[PDB]
Image (tube, coloured by chain):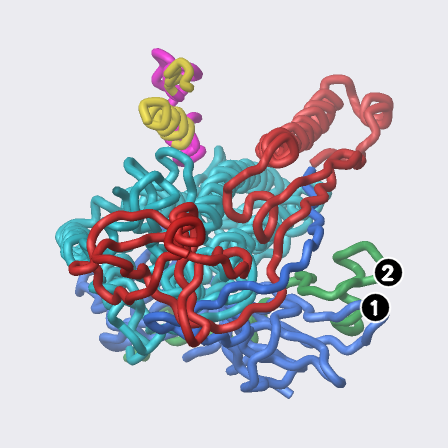
Chain colours: A blue, B green, C cyan, D red, E yellow
Amino acid sequence: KNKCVNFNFNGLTGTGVLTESNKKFLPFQQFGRDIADTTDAVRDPQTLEILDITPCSFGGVSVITPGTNTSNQVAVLYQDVNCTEVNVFQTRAGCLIGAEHVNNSYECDIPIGAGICASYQTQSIIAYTMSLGAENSVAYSNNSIAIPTNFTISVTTEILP
Amino acid sequence: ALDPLSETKCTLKSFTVEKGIYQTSNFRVQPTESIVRFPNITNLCPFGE
Amino acid sequence: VSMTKTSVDCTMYICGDSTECSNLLLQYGSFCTQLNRALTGIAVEQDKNTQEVFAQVKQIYKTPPIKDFGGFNFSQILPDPSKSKRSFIEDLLFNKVTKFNGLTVLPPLLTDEMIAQYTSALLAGTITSGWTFGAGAALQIPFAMQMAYRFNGIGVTQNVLYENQKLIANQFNSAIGKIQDSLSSTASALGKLQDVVNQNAQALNTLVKQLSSNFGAISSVLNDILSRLDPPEAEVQIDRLITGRLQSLQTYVTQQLIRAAEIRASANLAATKMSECVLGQSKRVDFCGKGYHLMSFPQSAPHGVVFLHVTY
Amino acid sequence: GAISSVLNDILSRLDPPEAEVQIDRLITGRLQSLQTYVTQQLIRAAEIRASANLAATKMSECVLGQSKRVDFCGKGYHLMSFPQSAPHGVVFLHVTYVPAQEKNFTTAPAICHDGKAHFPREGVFVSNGTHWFVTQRNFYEPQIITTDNTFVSGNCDVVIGIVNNTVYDPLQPELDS
Amino acid sequence: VSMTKTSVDCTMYICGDSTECSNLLLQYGSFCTQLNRALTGIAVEQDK
């Protein structure tokens, strides 16, 4: 169980992972299908055991890399999986190999996913939760005000196609 | 196929790689074992007769 | 604002667990390369739409300890930090919404917790500072004097504001209870968001059902036509399943890209109303709904945003 | 799906009943390549045309006038703008009004002179420790209290948080002096 | 503001009044249904 094997249950060949669930088979049915009408669950020919056919794990592989004129260290990223059967830390988006997790929050330079970003600071790729901005407590009161006494005429630049 | 540092240069088609996250390839678990479980045997078939 | 970040691999969808399928898939050239980069480029733009609407300022503002804003009850608008940090209105919006098959669903960069934290930074900026926090520094101003510039901007004397502080406070708090009774009774008020979910949930399940078609062959399973038939006979039936699923994958990219361009014009419209109606006093007629605009209160929403416009 | 990508190699080598299958797969294979080029260049041009309507608005409203829309001509209060030429685009030069320094003060909504409430036309009363004066919200400018800067409206018995002061009428240096 | 509400049927355009044509038309899955629901969804947006 829990392995990507080539199952063979009464001629039903294929490749899948034998997992357990709460699905209870009917005494006349021998196999179950998903919405794609494929091999989704098989029945144990020896006893009353329900073994669902789970497809094996796959996902996209991304590389967190800085600029060429900055550094050359990289990290391996895996999507929508955990660090179970894939120096190595678990993030909210997936399993990351090659980066360390830092509890301190910084500015998002290179995004990872699910509120996690990465950056190169003095000298390795670190994983951290991104910050949404600096803390600014407004001094609210019944008569307190902040009227500007000095102004700066700054010119902004906007580029639109 | 050497390292993920040079793997980013193949999917980008550029020597100078800027900062960011780039998708290079995909992984997949390969099958190793095979399940050939079947019920037990009670007797022998009379094919010799 | 945003949509579902669905990333479908072009290789493992048509040729999942097959060897002869990958030999005929590379004969099309860069057809699978363009479909993978198109679905990847959409999901980057879905995270950019949330940064242009919610992330308007570079500072995070907190709630003041003084909750007496001239008689107005803002406990239903501001989120509760003692519980996810969501208010009572935001709880009714997330509770009224609706694996390894080649369709990988990626989570967004801006989570629903950080959306409400970006919403609470704009709620404290509009109430305690008005439009000064978006145009410059966090200039503090009382809420009784904040509405004095709002009534004078539309041609109403500010003498009626201070003499009727308790009159307009009971009318405002009674209007919030009508919204909470409408959202908790039925989910018909979320029709602007349910059209985005139904175009992303039914279209995702359609691609799982499109691979079961034979496309003129005997069976859709690649193992039942390769190991059971002749290799001259298996070359035709695999190519019918490859070309039959390639047009199904090109249809899913084309239909979602127009919906991504539709959601981008809605995100730029939501970023316009956040920068003008929420982050200031707009004199544009029917920009914050029917009536003279005074203020606005944004709310968090699953893959969207909900505005609570205040009219006169 | 064909054996080659050259149109001349299939017709010369294979039979003319057999070459028409691989040629039509190359035509339909390049037709789907043209369907991708037409569709992707039309959806992306719709986003440019949606951005061209925004670029034409900021060159006809923000440049040819003073827009009161917040965060439309950039951050801050809009003064003027200057467009410049750019290849396949435009670069804006928005001149805005950004404050630099501010101080904390004590305010009051209105004052009382002889029983009636005096509200300012644009601004609020600010006390410096001794008395209130008339000033603006955008710029700090201490001015005297007069009828030209204030407005008589309401009474001094129903306004919550009101204070008392003395309105300096311009007829008082001429008659009451 | 709006345009004409043209809803072209997927079945009658290709396999109009034919029985054996529907066996080669419905074998491609719900691609015929996606052409009808897309043109129906435009006519809903034309009314909006």
Q: Is residue D158 above or below residue E48?
A: below
Q: Which residues are magenta?
A: E10-33
Q: Position of residue E22 (x, y in %)?
A: 38, 23
Q: Chain of mark 1?
A: A
Q: Quadrant of residue A153?
A: bottom right
Q: Position of residue E34 (x, y in %)?
A: 40, 32
Q: Quadrant of residue D58?
A: top right
For the N terminus of chain D, give its image quadrant.
top right
Identify residue type, mark 1: Thr
Magenta: main secondary structure: helix
| Depth order, front residue of C202/A46 | C202
What residue is disc 1 on?
A: A68
For the C terminus of chain D, give its image quadrant.
bottom left
| Depth order, front residue of C219/C276 | C276
What residue is disc 2 on?
A: B15
Mark 2, secondary structure of its residue: loop
User: Is E14 one of the magenta-colored residues?
Assistant: yes
| Depth order, front residue of C70/D103 | D103
Q: Position of residue D28 (x, y in %)?
A: 66, 26
Residue with the most extreme top position = E17
